[PDB]
Length: 152
Image (spheres, rainbow, N blue to C red):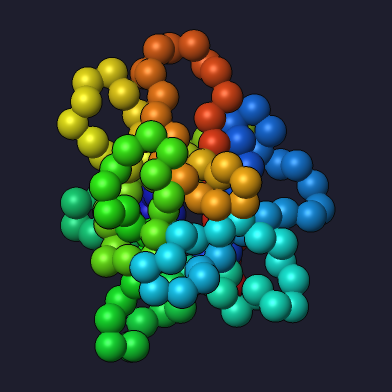
């Protein structure tokens, strides 16, 4: 094997420069159909909304879906229009590229494929809302948002 195995995971918001902040993480959190996915603490009113089924397609890309499966419709990380600072919404699951962060066994940049040359769209957070952050592929080694995937 290689890459992340299929399963149910919690996703904690970190960065490439600080992949392991310590206790007190903010986790991807569903908050209703077609609503923005948020970054919230692992606390009583949210825990059930913080587990995600991650699956790799024959493509090598992954969907991140809310709560296993079996409802009328599968909801997961998605986007209406992919634009800078647009929110990640719980919608028809989109496909993503997961890039393992150097020095870590389990932190990945969640990348949303787009046309644009020399541009990388990555899932980040702005005020506790997950959003698409656009970065130049500049070779700078600059800070990028990333996510620690821990098995549930």
